[PDB]
Image: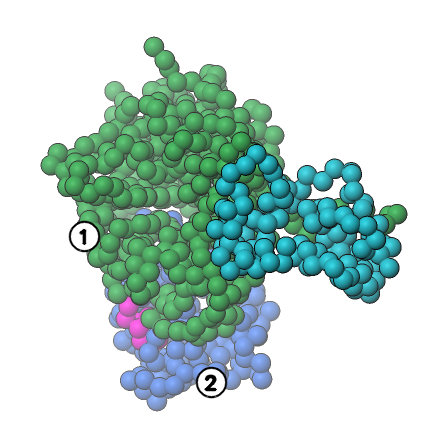
Chain colours: A cyan, B green, C blue
């Protein structure tokens, strides 16, 4: 994923085109085509890709609560880090749920073998 | 339908493809007629006796935007802004004579023309109904922060459409330079429309490219700091966008107008715009965010909400728009009415939030002339002259309510001292006879004392009512009365 | 020190007469505070004043006040406004400017925010047509009437105020002496320039 993001930063369109030219499938081309480009699409992410069913909706919440994060291989928070960002903004200064525990939770989410979290 | 002109020797200019057009005047003499003959000159024309059309050569290219401010004759001459604002004031109102009041925006292309002088008058028409309020509660004025007062001064400061930072070097009636330089966020790209008059003495602007992305360069700017200096703010207001792209079906909307109105709280004119028509509307309703779900259990923030949206069939928009928060049940006049001409022949004029249908009587850019619904024919048909349609205010008939609305708007025009063109709207002068009778009765009884400053004007108003016909008697009688009274009074 | 105010309003009513009055009353008044009108630096020097001349509602449905004269060095913009004031004003002859003098009061207000460190504030207003109207300001928060204006100009602040009208005398001087603080509207005289009107 790091190499893909670097290729995107370098050239972009050609890589996503070669990846989405033909074939009857649908991989996670959203977080790979809505990260950084000469187009904001900022509120678009809360609007369109925010289809987050209750399934694993509190998964990232329980993770940030009791990380102590690489227990089992699971990559779904990438397309669902919206709840993570919501909790972060609500605890940091918007509501003040955590003064310094927010930094601890961020460091826990900054655990090794996890780089996509930084991208999100 | 009615009131159409034509140009004999000139035509659609088949040699040049096209050119965007615009004009708008909330005061008297509301014809500007941006066009291309067969760059080109700019025209001015009055509402009465339009035979004597006038024009004057410009000194720039493409003449993109112009919009006057007050009854004082002026214009903007945008599109590299050569020959900037001035008055006419020479002998009459038929010669431009652009004076040395020029602001040198070197090789630019802004599309902004704004910064009016004072507040918008308040009209409690539905509640007051002008029974015996004597213009007290029927016509008021809400306290409004004047832009950079010192006495309310005013300049032609605008926003760089082509550029991306700001406008400076303001010299209003003082001939002083006051030159500075500001950074203005050091980055930007805009194709926006201006909305100036907000609560504080600030200006609002937001649009960049269209439906493709969702950027809005909200620039909350402050200009009044000290004499001989400028400190233009770079406050980024909360961003927003057109939620039209929520449809997974398609997203080809690409708006190109997104204009606003002088009331910066209750409109958002985003719209899907070849091969599309879908109006949208959002508000600025402040509300707190749902800070929850973080555990077992500053709220002041702004998140926009929807107002109205639907699928329609239209191409060209003209203009957006009394006050809101009124249960306008018995009211059927174009209160905050938003209409726009339809390409396919007839014009389906219908107020906001319903858009359903109105009477049609089966077998480029415009703006609303006034309360009386008589539009200007600058629709998407090429270099064609102006048109007018039925100003009928609502479906049903109500002669009492009709004359009531007529006297309301007449008294409004009187107190505001603007021009009046509700002539086409009123029926033959018999009803108008009863109207002026009731009007002078109320004037005499419940003046209570403004008569000593409001008499003369309304007498001339009387003339207009007696202008159209068999009843030409009162016309001449009132003219002689007015001229004799004036001459004797000044001789005293 | 020497905080004066210069006001004229008879432009709509009678223009040429002012030009005559300038030859005898306006121009000598300014020489009391300057060695001669030429072209000098302008700043907060105490002796500065304003120049306010407007019209009535007759043929101005979009303008009431456009005054701008903070210091003007007492020479340049003073002479300009004197010789380039206006030539308009029609309608009839019933009232030209009362709401103007109220705004004049407002001007004194800014002195309180500008002339910090008294100054024996003085003011002078000219108007040929006898004014009377119901509205008060239509421009700012303050509001009242001619009576309120005069009691503010006299009692609220000891600003010496006079009215050097044309040789004719209307029914104005009478009511303008109802102030317990001495109004001193005496300086309407063909004799030479008074020391302090």
Mark 1 vs mark 2, CA separation in Å: 48 Å
Report the front residue among B407 and A110. A110
Q: In the rendered structure, does residue B103 fall within the stretch colored magenta? A: no
Question: Above or below — where is B288 with respect to A26?
Answer: below
The single residue placed furthest to the bottom in the displayed view is C35
Subunit ID for the residue under disc 1: B
The magenta region covers C78-84
What secondary structure predominates along the stretch shown in magenta? helix
Tell us which disc is closer to us: 1 or 2: 1
C82 magenta-colored: yes
Circle on res. B472: none
Residue extending farthest to the left is B9
- Residue in the foreground of this view, choosing between B228 and B411: B228
Residue, x 31% and y 55% (percent of image)?
A: B78
- Residue sitting nearer the eye, A40 or C144: A40
Q: Is residue B185 visible?
A: yes
**Helix or strand or loop: what does disc 1 sit on?**
loop
Query: For residue C45, which numbered disc appears in the image?
Result: 2
Residue drawn 35% across and 37% down?
Answer: B366
C82 on left or right of B130:
left
Subunit that carries the residue with mark 2:
C
Q: Which mark is residue B57?
A: 1
């Amino acid at each position: 994923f790091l190499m893909l993001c670097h290729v995107a930063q370098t050239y972009g369109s050609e890589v996503i085109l070669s990846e989405s030219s033909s074939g009857e499938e649908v991989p996670f081309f959203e977080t790979w085509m809505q990260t950084c480009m000469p187009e904001e699409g900022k509120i678009l992410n809360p609007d369109h890709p925010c289809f987050r069913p209750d399934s694993t909706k509190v998964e990232s919440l329980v993770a940030l609560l009791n990380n102590s994060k690489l227990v089992q291989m699971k990559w779904h928070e990438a397309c669902l880090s919206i709840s993570a960002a919501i909790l972060e903004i609500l605890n940091a200064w918007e509501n003040g749920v955590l003064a310094f525990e927010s930094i601890q939770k961020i460091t826990d989410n900054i655990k090794g073998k996890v780089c996509s979290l930084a991208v999100c | 339908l009615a009131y159409v002109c034509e140009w004999e020797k000139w035509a659609k200019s088949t040699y040049c493809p096209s050119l965007p057009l615009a004009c708008a005047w909330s005061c008297r003499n509301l014809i500007a007629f941006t066009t291309d003959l067969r760059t080109h000159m700019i025209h001015i024309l009055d509402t009465e006796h339009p035979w004597e059309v006038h024009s004057v050569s410009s000194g720039h290219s493409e003449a993109i935007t112009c919009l006057e401010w007050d009854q004082s004759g002026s214009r903007l001459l945008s599109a590299d802004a050569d020959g900037q604002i001035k008055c006419w004031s020479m002998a009459d109102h038929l010669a431009n004579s652009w004076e040395s009041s020029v602001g040198s925006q070197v090789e630019g292309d802004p599309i902004v023309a704004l910064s009016w002088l004072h507040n918008g008058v308040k009209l409690a028409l539905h509640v007051e109904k002008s029974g015996a309020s004597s213009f007290g509660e029927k016509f008021s004025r809400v306290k409004f922060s004047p832009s950079l007062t010192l006495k309310p001064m005013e300049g032609w400061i605008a926003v760089t459409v082509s550029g991306l930072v700001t406008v400076s070097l303001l010299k209003p009636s003082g001939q002083v330079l006051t030159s500075t330089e500001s950074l203005c966020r050091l980055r930007g790209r805009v194709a926006l429309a201006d909305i100036a008059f907000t609560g504080g003495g600030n200006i609002v602007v937001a649009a960049a490219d269209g439906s493709s992305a969702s950027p809005v360069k909200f620039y909350k700017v402050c200009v009044s700091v000290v004499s001989e200096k400028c400190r233009i703010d770079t406050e980024i207001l909360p961003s927003l966008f057109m939620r039209c792209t929520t449809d997974p079906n398609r997203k080809d909307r690409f708006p190109a107008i997104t204009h606003l109105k002088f009331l910066a709280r209750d409109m958002s004119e985003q719209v899907l715009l070849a091969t599309s028509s879908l109006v949208e509307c959002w508000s600025l309703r402040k509300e707190g965010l749902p800070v929850n779900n973080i555990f077992q259990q500053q709220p002041m923030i702004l998140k926009w909400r929807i107002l109205s949206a639907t699928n329609d069939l239209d191409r060209v928009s003209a203009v957006a728009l009394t006050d809101l928060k009124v249960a306008s049940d018995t009211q059927f006049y174009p209160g905050l009415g938003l209409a726009l001409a339809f390409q396919d022949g007839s014009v389906h004029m219908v107020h906001r939030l319903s858009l359903q249908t109105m009477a049609v009587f089966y077998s480029k850019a415009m703006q609303l002339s006034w309360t009386s619904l008589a539009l200007v024919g600058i629709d998407n048909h090429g270099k064609l002259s102006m048109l007018r349609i039925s100003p009928s205010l609502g479906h049903p008939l109500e002669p009492k309510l009709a004359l009531q609305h007529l006297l309301f708007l007449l008294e409004y025009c009187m107190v505001t001292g603007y021009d009046w063109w509700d002539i086409l709207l009123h029926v033959q002068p018999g009803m108008v006879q009863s109207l002026v009778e009731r009007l002078h009765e109320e004037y005499t009884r419940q003046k209570p004392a403004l008569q000593q400053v409001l008499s003369t004007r309304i007498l001339a108003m009387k003339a207009s009512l007696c202008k159209l016909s068999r009843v030409c008697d009162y016309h001449t009688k009132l003219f002689l009365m007015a001229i004799t009274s004036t001459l004797k009074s000044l001789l005293r | 020190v020497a905080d004066v105010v210069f006001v004229i309003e008879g432009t709509a009513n009678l223009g040429p007469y002012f030009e005559e009055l300038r030859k005898h009353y306006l121009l000598p008044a300014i020489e009391y505070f300057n060695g001669g009108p030429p072209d000098f630096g302008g700043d907060y020097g105490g002796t500065q004043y304003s120049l306010v001349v407007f019209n009535t509602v007759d043929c101005a449905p979009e303008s009431y006040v456009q005054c701008h004269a903070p210091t003007s060095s007492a020479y340049e913009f003073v002479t300009w406004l004197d010789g380039i004031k206006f030539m308009g004003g029609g309608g009839e002859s019933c009232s030209l400017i009362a709401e103007g003098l109220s705004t004049a009061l407002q001007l004194f207000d800014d002195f309180k925010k500008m002339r910090e460190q008294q100054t024996h504030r003085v003011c002078l207003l000219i108007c040929n047509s006898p004014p009377y109207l119901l509205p008060a300001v239509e421009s700012t928060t303050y509001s009242g009437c001619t009576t309120e204006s005069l009691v503010q100009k006299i009692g609220e602040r000891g600003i010496h105020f006079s009215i050097v009208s044309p040789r004719k005398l209307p029914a104005l001087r009478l009511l303008f002496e109802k102030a317990a603080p001495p109004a001193l509207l005496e300086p309407l005289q063909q004799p030479a320039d008074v020391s302090q009107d």
